[PDB]
Every structure is written in C-alpha cells, then in structure tokens.
Image 1 (spheres, rainbow, N blue to C red):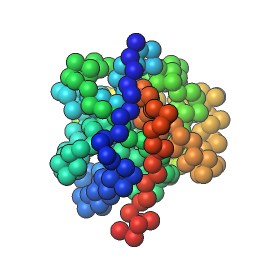
Image 2 (tube, rainbow, N blue to C red; image 1 turned 90 degrees about the horizontal axis):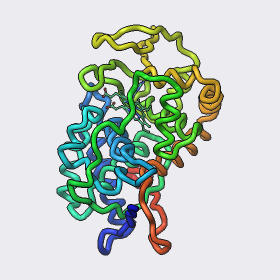
Image 3 (cartoon, rainbow, N blue to C red; image 1 turned 45 degrees about the horizontal axis):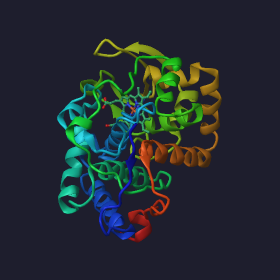
Length: 292
Ligand code: HEM
Ligand SMILES: Nc1cc(N)nc(N)n1
C-alpha cells in the first residue's frame, strides 16, 4: 500500500550534489590509513548496498529512501557489523551539508566510492526523504554468506534482481575484505582491493581454491595467493547459469562495468517513485576529471 515519492531537497541542483560528492571524494583521498591502507572506499560501497538491501518488493518496506540506518535497530543489525566505520566517515560530510537527506547521503557515498576507485560512472538521483524510527525494517533482511546458489538466487528475487544483476553486483567483492570480527570470515577477494576492476571473476575462474575452516570455525574458500571467497561467492561457479555470466565478465571489463552500473543504480533506487518532472539522473565528475 506504500509509496515513497522522491522530493528534491529544496532549491538544490546538480552543482549542490557535486559539492557533496567532492567532499566525500576528498575525504576518501585524505583518510587513507583506514583498514591497513585499504581506505574507506569499500566500506562505503557496502554501506550503500546494506541500506538498500533491506528492501522488500512485496510491500515496499525497507530500501534506501527513508535513511533508516541512522536508527539503532538497523545500525545494530548483526548483518551491519563494521558499517559504523562508514557512518562515522560520513558524519563530517553531513555536518557540512546538513540539507542532504540521510538516504541520499548513504547512497551517494557508495556512488562516490565506486567512481573514485576507478569504477564505472553510476548515475544517481536525489530526493530520498528521511522517514520516522517506526519505519525501520527489522533485522534479518540481509543475506547469509554460508549458503548455496539456490539461496542466493531466491534471496535476490526479493530485491527484483535476476541472474545477470546478481552476478554483476557480486563483482563488488573485488573490493575491501572480510574481517573475522565483523562477519566470521577473514581475508580479501583479490590483490587490487581498493581499485574497482573485474578481478573477482578472474580470481573465481583462475585461482586454485581450497575449502578450509577459518578461526571462527566457518568454511570459506582460500587460494595460495592469499585470496578468499565466501561460500555464496563460490556458488557463482558451482551453478551453471551463474558460471556462464562469471565467464562473460571475466572476459569483458567494459560489459561488467556497464552491467554493474545499471544494477547498482537500480539497487539504490528500489522502492522510490520518481515524478515524471523529477530531474534526470546526475552523473558526477570524479576529482581527477575536475583537476582536483
Ligand atoms: C549473497 C550476497 C552477499 C553476501 C552473502 C555478502 C556478504 C559479505 C560479507 C560476509 C562481507 C564481509 C564483511 C566484513 O567482515 O567486514 C562482505 C563484504 C563486502 N561486501 Fe558483500 N555480500 C553480498 C553481496 C554484496 C553486494 C551486492 C555488494 C555491493 C554491490 C557487496 C559489497 C561488499 C563490499 C564492498 C565488502 C567489503 C567491505 C569492507 O571491506 O569493509 N556485497 N560481504
Ligand atoms: N568483500 C570481499 C572482498 C574480497 N577481496 N573478497 C571477498 N570474497 N569479498
């Protein structure tokens, strides 16, 4: 029964949001020591996904619109352990630009991180509006990592994502790493973990993977190169339909970039009704493109 209409922050336009993008991007460059010099890019991408991934297509609950991660129930979701680091990073940004909504800020943080890490451009639309504490979705809507391809496929149907969209989105697991204290998994998915590339797919196909137990007594796939895959990551090469798509992205960087950009924008916009006369999506310039 539930409609969330995008409403542009009063009087704001592209230039306002480019300023917010720039402040996030400059801080990404500045605060470079975080997580053993990985920097904040990966955790900001994960934050944007987790605030969006609570969405349920069946009743339009959850989703990025309401900015509900700011409330303790969601902030404290065991599935969100570690994301507090991303939230703290964004605090001074919100202080400088207090007019931006929380959902706009969290989602823009993810777009900025992807682009600054040399990923694809992600078109982004403003107008998410903060909603009250009672609209916060319950814990348990984000996915488990110990499961198989059938679980992944069914899970993502709730977010209206198909096989191609799922495999494209999972390529973000090239970024950052798993941390034992956060999730019960430990290690990175590859070498270039603060640069956005198609390495996730190459590593799935090319590494010699061993099913091992980590120090939290959970199974994960490890390679001699020091990379790891979650059981749900590895499921993408166990299922024949996912495997074909993995091979496609391993062999076509541009196609992966284009498909990721579409799926990630869609993820960040699920649940939102944009008026016919809403502004077109914004495509922000990187700091590099601006000579900044
Ligand atoms: C089946 C679906 C997925 C599962 C089970 C899953 C699970 C996980 C787990 C367990 C971690 C480690 C968290 C930690 O220990 O800090 C992680 C990290 C991460 N995830 Fe996912 N994830 C999924 C999909 C996605 C998607 C769709 C995206 C975004 C498009 C994403 C982006 C990330 C990023 C960037 C990190 C690294 C964060 C950091 O380095 O701090 N994941 N994921
Ligand atoms: N988030 C990540 C990063 C990474 N390097 N590997 C995996 N499996 N997941």
